[PDB]
Image (cartoon, rainbow over all chains, first blue to last red):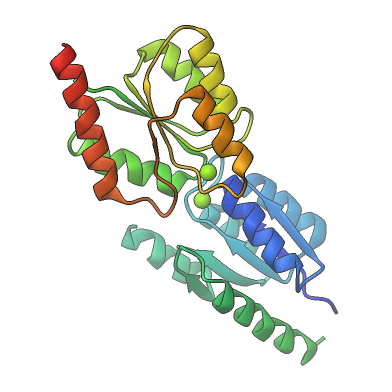
Length: 123
Length: 124
Ligand SMILES: [Mg+2]
Ligand SMILES: [Mg+2]
């Protein structure tokens, strides 16, 4: 019933910051540095929420999502957001939220709080 | 004629830095980690290094140390938004010419790069 969160950010500093802030309120938190690790961690822990970068090494956040969405799963998705092409594809994929960098902590935590309330309602 | 090497693990910031700089400097290289950064330095001997500190494989400071140990003396700009006093201390020992933490101020970056270009000019 706990909200499981997966963070996919290629920047070491930003990834660890996200992880630290989030784990302070949510125990089930995992983080990856590219779309491949991200896809593996997703299959391994089936997180409820995915917070992911778009441009990343090895595999982009959108190709990663497509591979995930193309497996049945329908997690809540927060996108860490320069070209309209990315946005548009992010819509086809079904992205739920777009968070502008520098990531704003309150908005993020507030959004996750919203995601849990929704999870309980359906458990 | 100022050759610049950018080392940053975040793709977005790395590509942004490459774009805004390439607009006014024709010789720019970008690396995603200290190891790749080190290899590119050895290949193209750039005059300027713009590097982050914490990255995969090899960190900016360790990278810088290896490059210096080899005898090169490039101008160095550190773009890390670190959280300790120890990174700063080691950075200064190695000899950094400018700390431009995130979020990066393009204006401050351009002026500094022009200063370096002038130094390489006056020195020919
Ligand atoms: Mg970085
Ligand atoms: Mg990134």
